[PDB]
Amino acid sequence: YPSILHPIDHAFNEYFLQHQLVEPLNNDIIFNYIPERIRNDVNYILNMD
Amino acid sequence: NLEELMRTGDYAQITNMLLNNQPVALVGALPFITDSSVISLVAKLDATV
Amino acid sequence: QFDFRASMHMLTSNLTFTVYSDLLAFVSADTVEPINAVAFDNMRIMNEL
Image (cartoon, rainbow over all chains, first blue to last red):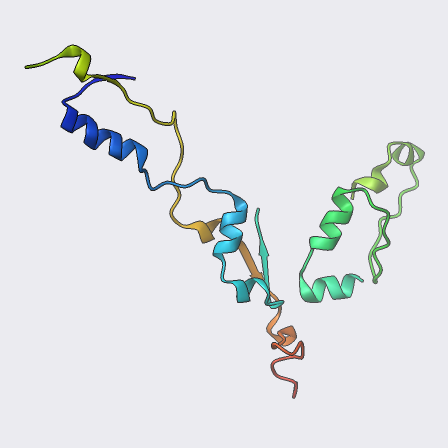
């Protein structure tokens, strides 16, 4: 989008745009988010429905 | 073995085999429906359960 | 002084995405019957039955 910004304002907004904290999320990330020893425990059945 | 599957609750193998149409034999005391309809057999209902 | 050339920028971002917080809400977690729960050595936690 076009924007009108003072160079300082542009610097701040561009830093915000270029350094966002959101990462792509998928089922592999969530599966690895589970503690590794609970994923290997046969007493717990973990599924991605 | 259906007893082992029910005890452990891990359906990964059976799910993969059913999704991939891999011939298998589910072994265990099972109730069954008796169907005398020829049209039902032609319609292949036994494969839908 | 305000300069249009020095103030006009193109701000770039993504069109849309959904941010999630509770990753473990995407995990369907079940457990075996406690009678069948086993320890690290693959034997039942309580064997006196």
